[PDB]
Amino acid sequence: STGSATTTPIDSLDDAYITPVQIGTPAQTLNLDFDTGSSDLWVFSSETTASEVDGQTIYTPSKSTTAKLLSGATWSISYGDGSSSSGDVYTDTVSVGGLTVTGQAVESAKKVSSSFTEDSTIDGLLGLAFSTLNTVSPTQQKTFFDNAKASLDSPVFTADLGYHAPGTYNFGFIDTTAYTGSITYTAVSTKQGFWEWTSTGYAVGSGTFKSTSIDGIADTGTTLLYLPATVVSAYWAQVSGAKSSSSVGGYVFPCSATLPSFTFGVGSARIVIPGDYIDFGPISTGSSSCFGGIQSSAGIGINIFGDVALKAAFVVFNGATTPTLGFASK
């Protein structure tokens, strides 16, 4: 089997991407944030504290003839951005782009943090990291991909995120028309539960490539590119007037600037992030100070190849017995 679904930016900045997901019988379609940095499929629901729902579409398990309470199971998750959610668990039928999993754990939120409430466009998350990170207790549950894997034509999914435009998540096949050149594959460590890999270096604009190993995670659920402070300083030094602002929470730059590109290495291959992908717009409405899309990972504890990086590539998440990651230009 295979599946193919379009993923759509939630706003004009590509702050996140939503993908429609069918849950239950009859189907209830929710728009979920596919997150290769976590491993829980959780949704706003009829159980979510009413004051914490503000415009989201909810899953109502009592209206699904295939929903079953997973007795005694609870979940609770905290994300790197400080947000969180928790609740109980159903199993139900879940379909993405024509690919169906029966008995998928659907984590129903009883509580969500303010950031989730305040974002009316995201109805929940669909985790695509390794199932070892799943938070369900006392019996850990499998991700949608893990459940689908054996049925897929090939044990892979691909992320093809757009810049200020829709893109595609495919399951079970590689669309050879979706990228240019070849796909370069690189080793993955699953030791921390992430799609963790090592970039071979970087360049800023038309500058020379610096060969240096940068361990980080391919994370579709993180907006920005978070890299070591040395790398980030080298980038922003090429933008007149750019500075790190403790008050704002990162590097800012004059909105009148033209940003240089940023290249990262995948083995001997190179992925170029155009400068415009690095612009996250005014820090507040009407400001002429703009927020940068490349930020320091110092104090995160890990480097994160988030959407800024991934949307410059066609990315293969290869879930073979020994997982790997592939990157192609597009």
Image (tube, rainbow, N blue to C red):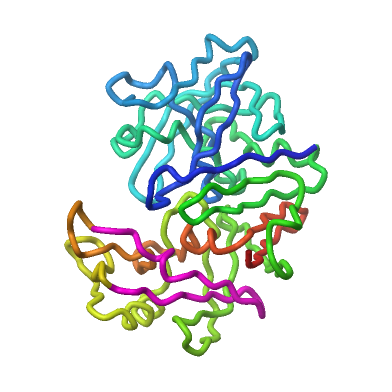
Looking at the rendering, in which quadrant would you find the N terminus?
top right
| On screen, residue 180 above or below 101 | below
Which one is in front, 302 or 31?
31
**Residue in view at x 56 percent, y 49 percent:** 36
| On screen, residue 274 above or below 172 | below
Q: Does residue 273 belong to the magenta stretch?
A: yes
Q: Does residue 16 belong to the magenta stretch?
A: no
| On screen, residue 181 above or below 175 | below
Range drawn in magenta: 257-282
Q: How many marks?
A: 0
**Residue in view at x 56 percent, y 33 percent:** 20
The location of residue 325, given as percent across then percent down, is 67, 61
The location of residue 224, given as percent across then percent down, is 41, 59
**Residue in view at x 28 percent, y 69 percent:** 251
Q: Residue furthest bottom?
A: 208
**Residue in view at x 21 percent, y 61 percent:** 248
| On screen, residue 226 above or below 47 | below
